[PDB]
Amino acid sequence: AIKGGYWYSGSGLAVSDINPSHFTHLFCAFADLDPNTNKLTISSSNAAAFSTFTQTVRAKNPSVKTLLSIGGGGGRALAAVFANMASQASRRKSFIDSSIQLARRNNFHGLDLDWEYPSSDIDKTNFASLIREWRAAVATESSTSGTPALLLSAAVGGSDQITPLKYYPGEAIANNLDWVNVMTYDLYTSDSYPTLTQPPAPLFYPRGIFSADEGITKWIQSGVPESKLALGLPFYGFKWRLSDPNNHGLFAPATQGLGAVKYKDIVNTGGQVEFDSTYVTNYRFKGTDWYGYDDTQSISAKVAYAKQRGLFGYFAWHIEQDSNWALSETASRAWG
Ligand SMILES: [Cl-]
Ligand code: NA
Ligand code: NA
Ligand code: NA
Image (cartoon, rainbow, N blue to C red; front, side, top):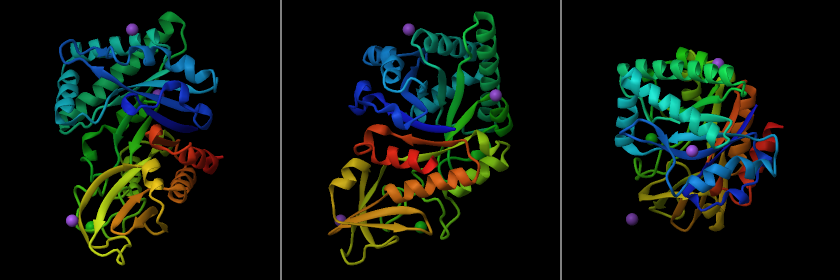
């Protein structure tokens, strides 16, 4: 049911170059949360693109649905801002009201909350209040205006490796959001694990305790039904420098991390591509350069996993990182 794609406004991909044929849902990232008013705002840079996002994409795929994403991975400061907004009923009200009005005023079908991350039992309770009040406002605004109701989603931590999932209210999510975008990636980055090559977003991780499978299982255990979970797919990976170009498998000795790299830039490298079916990851190497990332095989494998578990679907972060829609096409084809 969801073939999701995030369009990151700072990516350089123009809205008119998006191919919405491979998606059911497109997220326009990100509106900003104003710390002063606690209103959802759009930067003057984004206003023209956001205001025509939906009209533009629907010219190519009229059945595609759009949502305005709010927040971002903006560090602890942005988390603080969401946290303080969520703490008071009147702040939540400003955010709720402005988010709905902004979605309507800019022809979005929905809103996507990206608070990274609730990080206390109080954050948890406030998150539940925020989303119940948001659902209530969305149902009221829809009934009072006659306008078809906004969709509500949230992007959520995808593993205890990323953030303690105990600080999400699973039951409040199940009853109040239409689905969640489970961020099942960035588990084993080259910045955090610089001395051994890793699968950064492995489906399974039998040498440890965290994986996409662990995260999905925890979300289901936490009170969210599989039919409200969308599996996250990263369109980028991480790079390491190998100690020895001849020692180039998973968990190979590395001298350091060399950052994150878009899929489209990994494919550029050529070299040798491999697929590990135990962890479900691709990797690619040339000389001492090593990349751990999702290529078409692991994308297909993750999408098949999602479909077999009865998940709602999948989403990609983010679409500009793809190469000629290769991963987007692969994921859509895998789902059917
Ligand atoms: Cl490890
Ligand atoms: Na507006
Ligand atoms: Na609902
Ligand atoms: Na080095």
